[PDB]
Amino acid sequence: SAQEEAEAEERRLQEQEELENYIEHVLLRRP
């Protein structure tokens, strides 16, 4: 159980963009 960890942390980047884009999409669309 070492590789799985590498992914568990990767989420930190996924969630970041997941939220950063969630606003950019709604904003850019409805400025």
Image: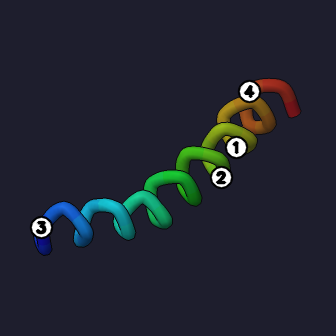
User: Badges 2 and 1: C-beta atoms under 8 Å apart?
Assistant: yes
Q: Which residue is mark 2?
A: 20
Task: Report crowding for label 3: few under 14, some 14 to 19, many 20 or more residues within 10 A (C-alpha).
Answer: few
Q: Circle 1 sits in a helix, a strand or a loop, which is it?
A: helix
Query: Which residue corresponds to the image point at 65% horizontal and 52% vertical from the top-left?
Result: 20
Left or right of 11: which side holds 24?
A: right
| Distance CA(mark 2)–CA(mark 3) | 31 Å
Q: Which residue is mark 3?
A: 1
Quarter of the view holding residue 14:
bottom left
User: Badges 4 and 3: C-beta atoms under 8 Å apart?
Assistant: no
Give the mark nearer the N terminus: 2 vs 4: 2
Q: Position of residue 26 (x, y in %)?
A: 75, 30
Looking at the rendered structure, the kind of residue marked 4 is: Arg
Q: Which residue is mark 1?
A: 24
Looking at the rendered structure, the kind of residue marked 3 is: Ser
Left or right of 7: which side holds 9?
A: right
22 above or below 16? Answer: above
Q: Which residue is mark 4?
A: 29
Q: Foreground residue, 4 or 18?
A: 4
Q: Circle 3 sits in a helix, a strand or a loop, which is it?
A: loop
Give the mark nearer the N terminus: 4 vs 1: 1
Task: Report crowding for label 2: few under 14, some 14 to 19, many 20 or more residues within 10 A (C-alpha).
Answer: few
Q: Circle 2 sits in a helix, a strand or a loop, which is it?
A: helix
Query: Which residue corresponds to the image point at 42% horizontal and 58% vertical from the top-left?
Result: 11
Q: Nearer the viewer, mark 2 or mark 1?
A: 2
Q: Nearer the viewer, mark 4 or mark 3?
A: 3
Looking at the rendered structure, the kind of residue marked 1 is: Glu
